[PDB]
Length: 148
Ligand SMILES: [Cl-]
Ligand code: NA
Image (spheres, rainbow, N blue to C red):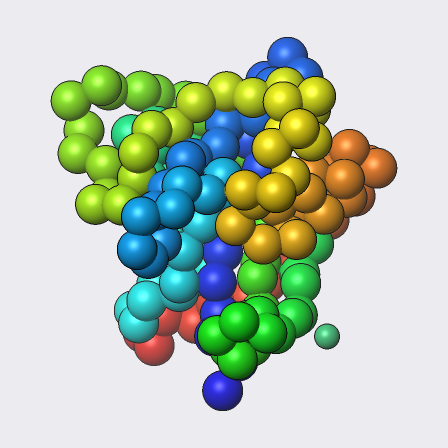
């Protein structure tokens, strides 16, 4: 009954790959590459899929950084967000980005903090803080069964 989501913390030389997105209406929000788990996939693969679909970069997950369980008061919806850190290992500017993505770009911590009011949720900042705090957990905490 909570919605399972995934998000990627992608840091390269003290900048983070984030998206500016319009989730509803017209307002631009800042967020990690992120989205809902879909049937038929593992959580780690959902994370890589979201990075590719939202940014046009391919992702190599390395660690779990945290799992966040919260309720968005504005939409009454409870989420369980599995957040991973990893590398980006390819980029192709012609890859189509999901509708609703304005642009994907690299932001420094100062820029992210100054944009706090337009963060999609409080988790945008929290996920980065936890990553910066050295929170790194093995991917193999998760065991997926594909149904073979
Ligand atoms: Cl919990
Ligand atoms: Na395993």
